[PDB]
Image (cartoon, rainbow, N blue to C red; front, side, top):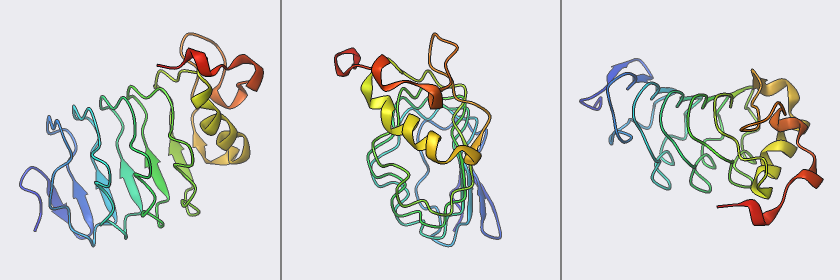
Length: 161
């Protein structure tokens, strides 16, 4: 069964461009491609994607996400495509990508990355180790500095919200 707000074909579920404020329920566990882009999603509930063990692509770009729950991608071990550009993210939870050994394309640009805060260090270190995976270049909010180019000295735990 296809979520009533979305359109389904094969293993592709298209929930894009539907003025959604939240992730639809009832996304089938056989889903391989999930489009959620161009909505007004402000948060992800913890564990929202855990049943989608076959998911290879998650398109979250052009939303209003201000953070990601810890572990939100942990069960998506086949994930190769993760698109999160044009959101309101300030950091990535530590270890968020640990299980994602099939990841090959990730979009992080057009987010207000908070590089003064030491929570940025997981993302900046991960980018330094997986350079070919980033599509485009995430940049620190208010500066010319690519997130991958953040120096550890420049960060501080006291500059975090």
